Image (cartoon, helix red, strand yellow):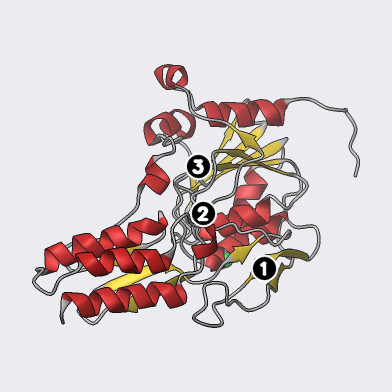
Amino acid sequence: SSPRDNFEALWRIMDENYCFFAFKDVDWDDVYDRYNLLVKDTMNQYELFDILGKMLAEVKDGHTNLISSFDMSRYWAWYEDYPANFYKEIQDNYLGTDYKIAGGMKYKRLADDQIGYVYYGSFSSGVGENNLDYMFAHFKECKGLIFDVRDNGGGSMLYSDRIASRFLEERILTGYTQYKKGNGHNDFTQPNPVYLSPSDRTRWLRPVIVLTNRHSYSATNDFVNVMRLLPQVTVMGDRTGGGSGLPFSSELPNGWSVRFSACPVLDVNKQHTEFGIDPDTAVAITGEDIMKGRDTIIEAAIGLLLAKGDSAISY
Ligand SMILES: [Cl-]
């Protein structure tokens, strides 16, 4: 397995399957011409790995990686160029030690029991129908809900759909999917509509604040995409980390593998969500709030939900 064969195979895999060339400042043909002069069959496996990793970093994509048995290439400036906007130690001041555990959820009432707070760290940690019903019943008397998915790198779409379906009033269009039809960079199938139906179990139609950060991505990005379509939902924090939760993976002749997003996911306006979704209200954790043991994002969400409107029960 020669370096030039692995260079050729990797360039071709990207050329024919990478979905987002239209949104990148580089031309993949000029990337071929440049790296063609750099890859030599005298290179050892480490030199080849560094150069091919740099080649993938040309598309500046946090979702693209080259994986060998010794390293994984990454463009993590995609995540690291944004503030953390989440600290477990500051979150401990809100959850304490007496928070409740229902599957993959941590939950507790805040602000004199007026606000329900949920932290859902991973879509890989399952949530059952009873877990959700019990969490909602604990928050029966609450004015609103905080659903915090900051630092949630995704996981299973089964839990994504199961949680999101609890906030629906009726069946809705959630967005669209496209898939690579051919080798051409823009050779996609027509946008396919994806729908979600409301749950038959306990639903939450009261105000909701969804908390996001750059470390909210993949299945979490798709979850956020559905939640921001709902009238009772406000998304707060920072731009999500994007991605789709639907990866492409292929092996190289040398056994290394390349991965990236397999399909473009579009919102209801047929706009790409791959590069992340902006919150409704941008809020960043401040240096002085950390010093006070406060989470600026949780506090802004509490403030917004407590902001009193009319004293009327209506529709
Ligand atoms: Cl269940």
Q: Is residue 260 left or right of residue 258?
A: right
Q: Which residue is mark 3?
A: 213
Between the residue at mark 2 and the residue at mark 3, the CA separation in whole angstroms equals 10 Å
- Please tell me how crowded label 2 is: few (under 14), some (14-19), or many (20+) other residues with Cα within 10 Å: many
Residue shown at 21% from the left, 68% from the top? 68
Q: Position of residue 30 (x, y in %)?
A: 38, 64
Q: Name above or below for residue 24 compared with residue 215.
A: below
* Rendered image quadrant of residue 40: bottom left
* Rendered image quadrant of residue 29: bottom left
Residue shown at 29% from the left, 73% from the top? 257
Q: Name above or below for residue 60 compared with residue 90.
A: below
Circles 2, 3 touching at the beta carbon (< 8 Å): no
Residue shown at 76% from the left, 48% from the top? 205
Q: Position of residue 69 (x, y in %)?
A: 17, 68
Between the residue at mark 1 and the residue at mark 2, the CA separation in whole angstroms equals 15 Å
Q: Which residue is mark 1?
A: 176
Note whether residue 262 is visible: yes
Between the residue at mark 1 and the residue at mark 3, the CA separation in whole angstroms equals 23 Å
- Does dot 2 land on a helix, a strand or a loop? loop
Front-most of 261 and 118? 261
Residue shown at 47% from the left, 35% from the top? 95
- Give, as a three-letter code, the residue at label 1: Tyr
Which one is earlier in the sequence, the residue at label 2 or at label 3?
3
Q: Is residue 167 left or right of residue 116?
A: right
- Which of the numbered marks, if any, corresponds to residue 242? 2
